[PDB]
Image (cartoon, coloured by chain):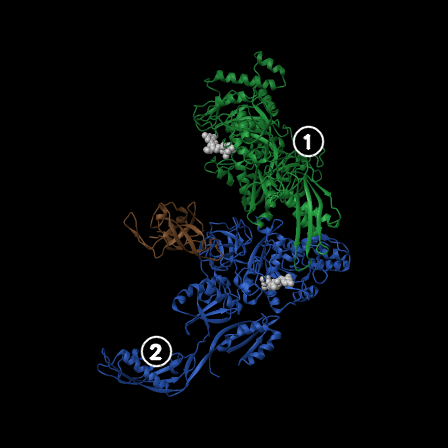
Chain colours: A green, B blue, C brown
Amino acid sequence: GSVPTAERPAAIRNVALVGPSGGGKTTLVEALLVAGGVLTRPGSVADGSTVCDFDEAEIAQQRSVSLALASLSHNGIKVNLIDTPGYADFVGELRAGLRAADCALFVIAANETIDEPTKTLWQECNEVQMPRAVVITKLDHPRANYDAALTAAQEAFGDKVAPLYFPVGDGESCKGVVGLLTRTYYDYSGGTHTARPPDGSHDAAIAELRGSLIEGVIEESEDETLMERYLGGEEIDEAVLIADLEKAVARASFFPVIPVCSQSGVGTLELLDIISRGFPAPPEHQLPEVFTPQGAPRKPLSCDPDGPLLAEVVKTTSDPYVGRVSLVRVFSGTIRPDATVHVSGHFSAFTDTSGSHGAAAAADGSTHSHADHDEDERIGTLSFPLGKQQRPAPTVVAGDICAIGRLSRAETGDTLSDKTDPLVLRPWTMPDPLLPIAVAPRAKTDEDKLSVGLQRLAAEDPTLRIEQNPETHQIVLWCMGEAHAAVVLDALSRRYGVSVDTVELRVPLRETFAGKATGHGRHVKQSGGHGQYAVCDIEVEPLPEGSGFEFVDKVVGGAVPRQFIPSVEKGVRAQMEKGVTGESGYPVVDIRVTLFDGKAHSVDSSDFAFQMAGALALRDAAAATKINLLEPVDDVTIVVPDDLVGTIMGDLSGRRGRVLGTDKHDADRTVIKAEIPEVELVRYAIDLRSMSHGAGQFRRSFARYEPMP
Amino acid sequence: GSVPTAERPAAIRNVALVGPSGGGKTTLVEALLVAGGVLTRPGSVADGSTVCDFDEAEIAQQRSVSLALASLSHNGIKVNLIDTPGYADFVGELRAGLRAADCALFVIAANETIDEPTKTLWQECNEVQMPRAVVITKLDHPRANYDAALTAAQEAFGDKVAPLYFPVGDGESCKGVVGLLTRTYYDYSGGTHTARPPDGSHDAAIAELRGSLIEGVIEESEDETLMERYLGGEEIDEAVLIADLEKAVARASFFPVIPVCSQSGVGTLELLDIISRGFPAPPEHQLPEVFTPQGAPRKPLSCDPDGPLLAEVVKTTSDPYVGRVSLVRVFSGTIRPDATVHVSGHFSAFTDTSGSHGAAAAADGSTHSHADHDEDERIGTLSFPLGKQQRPAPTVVAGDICAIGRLSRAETGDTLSDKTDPLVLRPWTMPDPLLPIAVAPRAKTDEDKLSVGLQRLAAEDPTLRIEQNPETHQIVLWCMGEAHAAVVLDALSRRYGVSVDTVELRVPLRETFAGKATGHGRHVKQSGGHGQYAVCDIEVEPLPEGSGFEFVDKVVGGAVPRQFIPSVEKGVRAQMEKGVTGESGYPVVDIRVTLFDGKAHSVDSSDFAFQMAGALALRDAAAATKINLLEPVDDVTIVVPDDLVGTIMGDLSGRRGRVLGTDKHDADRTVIKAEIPEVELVRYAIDLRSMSHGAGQFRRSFARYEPMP
Amino acid sequence: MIQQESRLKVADNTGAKEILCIRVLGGSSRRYAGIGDVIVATVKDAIPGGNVKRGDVVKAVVVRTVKERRRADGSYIKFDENAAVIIKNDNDPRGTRIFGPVGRELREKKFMKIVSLAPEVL
Ligand SMILES: Nc1nc2c(ncn2[C@@H]2O[C@H](COP(=O)(O)OP(=O)(O)NP(=O)(O)O)[C@@H](O)[C@H]2O)c(=O)[nH]1
Ligand SMILES: Nc1nc2c(ncn2[C@@H]2O[C@H](COP(=O)(O)OP(=O)(O)NP(=O)(O)O)[C@@H](O)[C@H]2O)c(=O)[nH]1
């Protein structure tokens, strides 16, 4: 159909659809687009004809793995649908979609109840005070009980959840719904949407539903006399109730329930009407706090095309022919083609908190550690995403989302604004991946481009963390889970031509002397030039942890020439650095070396010879005693339900974990604080999601180093 | 970076770079491509690692022998650099590339003066109105005199040649060039291009160059008040001046001079800018006149992707794996895969003109002289050739050159158009070869496939002509020179396995009678079938050349049977066909046989008998007088420069030649009317071209026969 | 009747010319391969610049045989040479074009790609 174009931010809606993995979100989006006229017939995820599930990975996994955007205009109101994956491994994409949205939509099926991942998704949506609306789908399923799921929703997320539309079906294929506020029964039995008054088969239940909905809304209505009036017998006007419901939903105070038949197309039209009326506008939505480049807080801009230019890229995609396709979320100002705009790369200062080992701020890619970058780029032709097709856009007003190609250095999450007024929207919450994945490149040609490919990968996916080990010299990919790790590996192996092989993550270790010992170092070599002769008799004794390297001089009579003692010290330091345990010795710290005697030659004494003699003496002293191996430990804070406390505690008991305390996270979850050695945490996430029906959520942070038990 | 794929022909440019053999065309192409970012580092011709220098013949000859195409992207504008052979033996490939491109680049060395081959190539570029931009390369040479080359180009190639950019260096490694129109000096001394204001050491010279360039450009512009403004002291705007320079260069009026330092990368970026802005556009360039399939001309077609489908092949070769690499140049309409295009063989009628004597129209190959065929073939995969590896092309808009595989009947230069509306463009005028060579098969099986092998080679090599001689019973291959002959023989022995050895080419020859005589033929053969015995008496007289064979019978009383007169006749015809001068008797011509007497037997008369009787009578008649040999003198139209007419007079004097006139062909060359024996014309073309340095063109046409001197 | 140590011509773009049959897949101790039978082979001759080189173990399907083969209709098919097509694990060709005719047995063995790409199916 026609390209949905909006000229005022009020007429634009940006709602992110969320839910469980495979909740039929893609089918719902296809049905809505067909109802919008863009698509002639509804696509099917199984057939792969859907607009949303167009990427290779989505069809390969037969489930949403990456988020997509669709644009629709209905009743003169444009809606920017944001379908997001429903699996925990892709939580960061869902959060990014939430940030770029002014509302949250939950697509759930009546035949299955609310799972714990859906509850955590509701919590995540709640902790931005986002408005949430409940959409029941898959009503064609035989086991689809709208009443049971509705109840569960009403009981779980407080009394603020009350249904808004009452379906009337046969229990197999819902033929239509009853409008509770409008007292109108919508019918689709003949294949046409017909709105007619209910015949009275549900009139008592309908009246009950209106009463409950009115009492719930009217409380949230500012008119406290409305409650009296309704309880006094006065019939509150339908338009007034509608407006009060719209305001309350814009206040993120109510969570209505609307049943939808994605397959049959039942309820799509009313659903679009509810999106266009009851949903908050970006002007109504509490726009995110906009910050100045230098960290000084700035007053948030009103959502208007005439205001100061303010936009934000929220997705980065790589295409072999088109190039980078960056989706830009605009909040204030107007974007016009060929204009030069300022690219604020997250200004990492706002994202430098925590980050564990990787200290991830934005776009990682250690050669690009932190983003914090500023650059002004001239944009090309504005476009809107329609699958792989890009509908050209004349101008981009505030409050809308657009796709821009050929962007050289634009990245996901970057704040776009006028170059004269650089701005910085508050960045989204980035989940920290805690599944390290060490890999090894197949060739140095791949390795050289590995930095560029990983930088671009983190530009596309801000949730992936990449850390290159400085001690073990291993490149390690931190991922959310099995699916996310697979996606990270595949995209690196294809989009950038970097052939890598996953290798074992090496946990850094430290070495120190376990006792006092002495070493005799001799370096005699008779080559074709000057002979070499240097002997050092050093004494190494243990030091308290963190004492570092101390040198004590006890040379008597100057047997070691005093010009070569610093060479002995340098050799000792180098030998500590190179390790003292075999061919794979870890750095030696917190030791003291006491050179008390030695031998030298009048002609064959050299600084290098004394360096070698000191290194060999240190090696002999290390071989003259035991060496302490120090392994690191990371504190782990876990949120798990109280019913599984014992299983996780016993699992940590088999994982040598030291329990620190069990803190009540809430009425049903307990925060568990414990420090676990990093070796035990290599596969902790996968086993935990097992030990928890996925409910297992934890964070880790390096604590200190301890010797191996 | 991103693969060069432009969505409009205006954002596509194709330049057929020209110059002498090993003039650095490839090297400059590599430098430009690295400037665009396609190649990591610019390859060297000698090393053979370049994209253009990949073929066996190009590497072996250490130069360009077959043209190559590369695609480049610059600021959203596609650039198609087309390296062309620098040797006149492959000037057919250069002519095709010029026909394949809308702009030509003269890659010449600053240490080399403009040779006559360069002047003739400039003339060929000139009388097709093909725009040219002067490029000065090899400035790193110790004898590299940029100013000398500039002045020589300005004096030779008309006053329209004038410097555009002024190089600045220390005389050994040029450190930069000065942008005259931009009044800015670009410096590469520090390893980075730096567009900075000039230091002022040559401000007066720069200003003079700016004034000269402006006044030259204004001359070809539209605003006639611009000259009065500039001469009146008013400073014309930089942007307007630029636009005027673009107009002057595009319209095939101006020839700006560009210094290029390919080795150090100096000037490549500004050359790319000049190609992108000041160079002509495929729509702007005067496209070849289009023709209807059935002989009628058609108005030139616009370079519009939405227009009628129109394209023309520019190279053809066979690959066992990917398929026939048919380099197809698109001019009008959009070419897409799975489309059936018209494969008209140039409809040669429109190119029967020009081509010197050979009527070179389509792919030459006198066995297939003039294609003039029709065909509609479904194309396979559209690919952008990058050396051997082909860049996939999902969509090919007009104004581009692409390689299409799996084209069964495609030949070089074949016009490709829509099946519903077949169209014929104007193909290039090809320099038909004039050096004959004879190939003898080692056996019969190779000769059986030799026909299809030579047909395929002629389809691949439009400039090559293959000739079969029925009189002397040999196959003759015509090549432009020596290197092209080596290339074509290698291709024949490799792509088709034609094992042959070079042999001398034999010219047609005939025999004639020098006197009158009578013959007596007596035959007696009494075999086991029908006894044969016949006697005939004929008379032969010498006749003027061109008289042909004649017979007069004057037998008296029917001595010989009338039924056997045809037998004798045909026997005499066969005997004179077999010759009379020994066992190597050449075909006797222009002789009249006059039968008068003979004897007959009751039973011994027979067809064969009388046949031999007449034969032996012919032998006896020929035995009494002399036989004169005649060689075919062919009219030779010698075209040499007027200063070289004296050389042709001197050498043709030693060639037993007679001069029937020296008509001035044009302002430089002179048509010479002369007839020369055929034996002298086997090597006339090669020596003519060698002495004329590429300025020699000539035609041959058999006129009559002359006796041995 | 291709079997152990038999030499096969290759009808692909992969760059190999001739392959040697190592094993006739499709059951233990199976002896012969006919049209439409998958075998393991080793490449003996190849284009120097091809993706497939000499000595690498590959998987192929027979498309032409010299030995006559009966069809359910009473008709018989025969070729002058034994030829095979390199395939990857999902029963798809590694090349992009097929040379020469193929028997229609491939149709009932579900080699749709080879059947579609062949110039002639008999
Ligand atoms: N009964 C029924 N099944 C549906 C419906 N929509 C999708 N499905 C089925 O559910 C599966 C995919 O559903 P869904 O998870 O929503 O697909 P997705 O959108 O790609 N994944 P996600 O929901 O996480 O975004 C398929 O097997 C599909 O046939 C629906 O409306 N009704
Ligand atoms: N010093 C110098 N040498 C060059 C330059 N360009 C090419 N050469 C050298 O000249 C030889 C080949 O040059 P060139 O004829 O331009 O190669 P080509 O382009 O493949 N052949 P052609 O010019 O006829 O198209 C090589 O030895 C190469 O190193 C240049 O700019 N400077």
Sort mark 1 into few (<14), some (14-19) or many (20+) by Cα contacts within 10 Å.
Answer: some
Question: Which type of secondary structure does the marked residue at label 1 adopt?
Answer: loop
> Please, which residue is most extreme toward the front here?
A557
- The disc label shown at residue B574, or none: 2
Q: Secondary structure at mark 2?
A: helix
Res B370 visible: no
Residue nearest the observer in this picture, B363 or A148: A148
Q: Name the residue type under label 1.
A: Pro
Question: Residue A477 or A576: which is nearer the viewer?
Answer: A576
- Local packing at callout 2 (Cα closer than 10 Å; few below 14, some 14-19, many 20+) is some
Residue displayed at 46% across by 63% down: B494
From the top left corner, tell me how far across and down residue A632 is, in percent: 61, 36
Q: Height in image: B63 above or below B655? A: above
Pinpoint residue B412: horizontal percent, then vertical percent.
49, 60
Q: Measured from the top left, where is residue B622 in percent x and y?
A: 37, 85
Q: Is residue A703 above or below residue A445?
A: above
Q: Label 1 belongs to which residue?
A: A300
Please identify the quarter of the rendering in which residue B602 is found: bottom left
Label 1: chain? A
Relative horizontal placement of residue A631, taking residue B463 as reference (left or right): right
Tell me whether marks 2 and 1 sit on the same chain: no
Q: Chain of mark 2?
A: B
Where does residue A579 sit, x and y in percent of width and height?
Answer: 63, 44
Above or below residue B285? Residue A63 is above
> Residue A113 bears which disc, if any?
none
Label 2, label 1: how many angstroms apart (C-alpha)? 110 Å
In the orientation shown, which residue stands out farthest toward the bottom?
B624
- Of residue B1 and residue A87, the one placed in the foreground of this image is A87
Find the residue positioned furthest to the top: A232
Work out whether A643 lies above or below A551: above
